[PDB]
Amino acid sequence: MLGLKTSIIGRRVIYFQEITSTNEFAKTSYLEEGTVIVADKQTMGHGRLNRKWESPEGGLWLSIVLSPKVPQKDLPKIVFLGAVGVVETLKEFSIDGRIKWPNDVLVNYKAIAGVLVEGKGDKIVLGIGLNVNNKVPNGATSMKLELGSEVPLLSVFRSLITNLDRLYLNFLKNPMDILNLVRDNMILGVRVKILGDGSFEGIAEDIDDFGRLIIRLDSGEVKKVIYGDVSLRFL
Amino acid sequence: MLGLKTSIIGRRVIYFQEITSTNEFAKTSYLEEGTVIVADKQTMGHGRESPEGGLWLSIVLSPKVPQKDLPKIVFLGAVGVVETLKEFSIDGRIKWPNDVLVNYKAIAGVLVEGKGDKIVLGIGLNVNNKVPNGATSMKLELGSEVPLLSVFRSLITNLDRLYLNFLKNPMDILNLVRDNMILGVRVKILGDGSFEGIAEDIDDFGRLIIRLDSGEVKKVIYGDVSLRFL
Image (cartoon, rainbow over all chains, first blue to last red):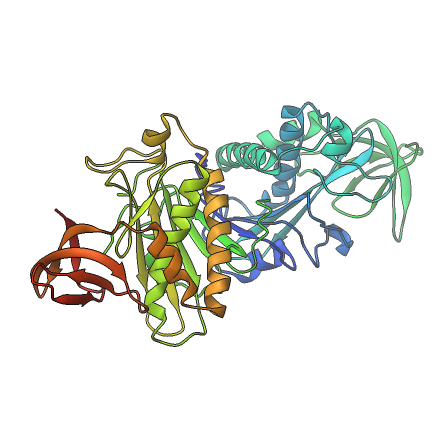
């Protein structure tokens, strides 16, 4: 009854009024490639770094089962597929989202969406959390807060799934293309701090061919970050 | 994302761009009660292709009621459809025991399957799809396309309410059927042979009461029997 015309992503959609986590269900259930898991609310949702991500009613909480027969090295680009997809959708609703490496989407520096990718050997789970009409944590934002009015969740869903299906299909053939899209929509040229042991500061210059964040320290040293906790030093 | 507010029917919904049969998938798969299986089209639909534009769905049920009441499940589907059609100002009427007609043309059919502790309620409703001759659709009746999703929301809400009351009082549905069924007309019953008579009413068991011209009263139980209007 949804009438989705996508090729792979969206051939099947499993909707829940409530669920612990769309990513968990997607990981533990055998599901055809392209199956989308979506729920009105998550009771135990979380983003990367195991950070508890509130998933109240009004938001778009979904996971997508993928099985991209591509080199084990391109798997890390799946996150970017989700982030670029969100950005393209936000644009369609006249909202300018920018990517905070590696998986966050911000608007005027406020978090509006997060992407959580989890591999499992037999498949890859692309999780996306987007603040639409739900109440958000202080410092965060939503499509509702940005546009000053409630947005039809299904309209956002339709838009996102369509963009992701398109991005995914091209990715299966031209895997490197996504990196350029990411660069054009990522927050760069700003000072950032990588947290944890061996913490350091520098300018986030770009992402390389593997998607690593290239940081230029004040000493001139160049470091390539694969993953971690990032903080904008002047925002 | 659908924001359904139902108690049981619709707690989960599995949508398919295409599927062989929503009823077959629901019967075969391990699914929780209330799960709705819906598809844009069925390539192998059937009753006792369903083209894009129609509403093709199946509901998994596990009613904890007497085995005798189980045969009443088909009526829940038929009444739910009638209620939804009335919400869209379409006069749906029930043709015993599983069909819904509008001006004597088929607009929807109900197929219930399942033996013990797992019942599948299948419903096919013509909304915006092309239909065979003799049949009709909500689009043909209203003169314009109808938001398929709106029809889905309406139907699921109606079925959930009807199903909850059915768990409490399995006989309540019979009154709704009676008020919305085509009666007082001559019909032909086809089964172990055939006979004609006036469809007078349905009894306390949902059996169709037929009065033959001889005055004889026959009570028809649905299963392997077909009804034709004269």
